[PDB]
Length: 62
Image 1 (tube, one colour):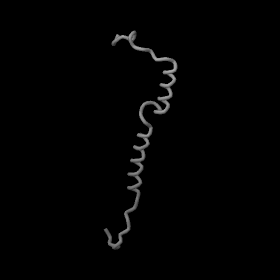
Image 2 (tube, rainbow, N blue to C red; image 1 turned 90 degrees about the vertical axis):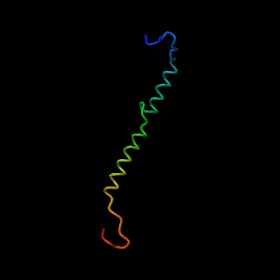
Image 3 (tube, rainbow, N blue to C red; image 1 turned 30 degrees about the vertical axis):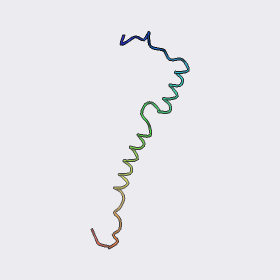
């Protein structure tokens, strides 16, 4: 085989349960937090575009 599973230590039943718990915390593999940040970045940009320009203190156009 690739190396030899015969020399590879097998995981115990308890170890398997812990592995599942870790996946649940990460949802799967990638951090869901990163995805949320990306969404927030786009939302902020859209909001800025929808935001009107600030009033001129001098009252001068453009």
